[PDB]
Image 1 (cartoon, helix red, strand yellow):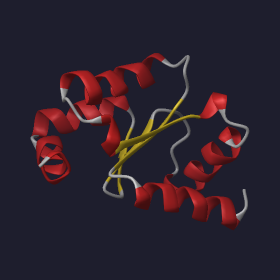
Image 2 (spheres, helix red, strand yellow):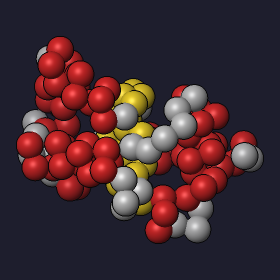
Image 3 (spheres, helix red, strand yellow):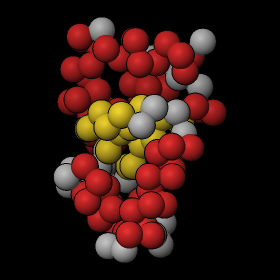
Length: 108
């Protein structure tokens, strides 16, 4: 994947408090998004959700994410530029108290 596509994905991560790369048919994507929006009440305005299967650039974005953080699958979640990972990683951060701390400045 090109360095310019990698830069673009880094720009999206920098431009959005929460960034999620998703696909519309993916159950773990739905779990993660529902956790953010429904359970944790994160406003939609704080989050960029890319449904890669609905984007011509989706495969390139996924390839860029692999180059950036080594992760292969969606969902792929960032919060304030920190790579969180997938749904299991999000749920772990709930249990450690780290997610509440990461979200506090976003929600305040």
